[PDB]
Image (cartoon, rainbow over all chains, first blue to last red; front, side, top):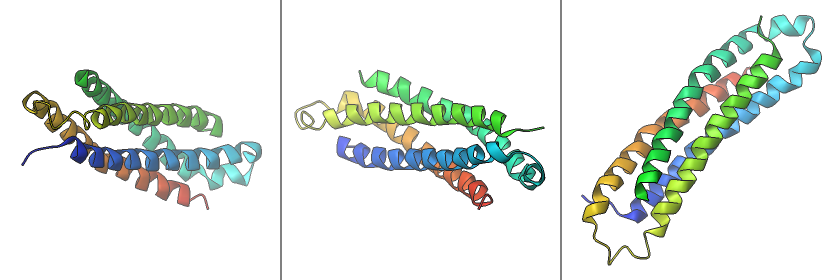
Length: 81
Length: 80
């Protein structure tokens, strides 16, 4: 087949949606973490130990992946110029 | 060992990385959009390459992004 700018616009929209949904969940999780700061004392610490481990591992590994995306897209956008 | 404070700074960098990705897709989409008016008269040949490349880049990363959402969502759900 052959690709039109209209076709890419549709895919781009899906990309924005996928990226925005990720942003959404990051904000949701950071809010959760943030709300714990005031009460990070006794039983609270033990209760959320697992979630904290999971959160650290996921966020840490997803950072450079996100950075690879923006780097790739930047270079491609640069090309269009 | 892990505090909400350290998770906060990590989360901050994560927000930044995702935000920068969203910035670049906005850039690229703006470029695509601008091509539509002069498309019919343009010479597609020299655009084919970057079209194919940009299509691949987006298509391969969309499901990765969605997976990230679903994973973070499950984690944030444990918080309820």
